Image (tube, rainbow, N blue to C red):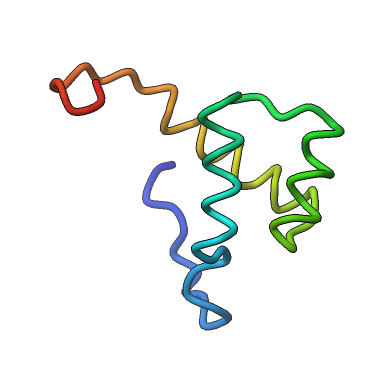
Length: 75
């Protein structure tokens, strides 16, 4: 991430929707690592493929890596 993502996407604003981000976050907060079977179960429920489950969790854990400890409302 260094002055990246300059390719302006006209195809769809948000790749995900409200219900998809519900299911994705619920799996993420119970376990930051979904196994091969948990990938498939999450995929059929969210209407996404395993490839889209890869992109979400790898990007999401990247932000999660920076332990900030900024305040009492989620460190």
